[PDB]
Image (cartoon, rainbow, N blue to C red; front, side, top):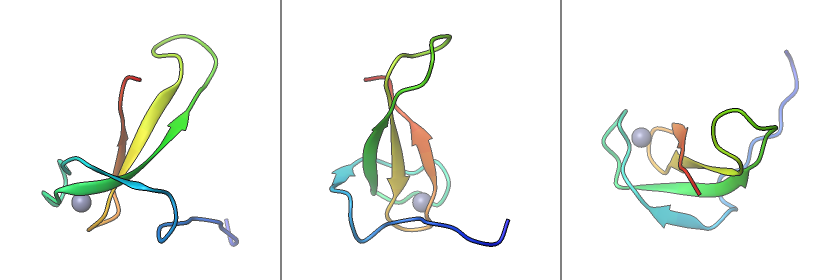
Length: 57
Ligand SMILES: [Zn+2]
């Protein structure tokens, strides 16, 4: 754990809320996995504290 590759200034942001700092917006992209919960999910990184969760589309 020494290098990294995160991005914020990029990725179109979407209007949402943050259950952590209470922000009112977050970044958003899709994240598909295998199959055992929700095919193709969208993570939303709040644009304030830097927290991200998942959607259902
Ligand atoms: Zn936040």
